[PDB]
Image (cartoon, rainbow, N blue to C red):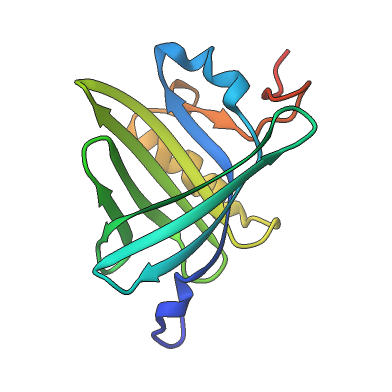
Length: 157
């Protein structure tokens, strides 16, 4: 905090932290991969953030641009039931956390996403995200961590 600036939000976003709940969670282990992202305001009444998930030594890499509308004060973008996610924490100086909620064909699934400007994520970003996670319902109940095991799979056991 010091002076207003849209750029604060605009920049590089690093997706590493994730939290979800789904019966198909087991199947979602393979899909797990490192994730990078970049946010930018689309000059057409839409805001978009591209994310490039790399994982050559396991599968490959994927990129996708998601965009729609965004709220003031902080950052919360809607994208039809199928895609609904809100950017919270502190996407103004270096660390931000965003929770995603999917809704399609009458199906509800929860998934969180954490965008970090720099690898050195502040204790607040991680702690507040985890702490905030509980306020919503819990942490492990809805947890997920950047994959780091065999091929395309998250560390476990």
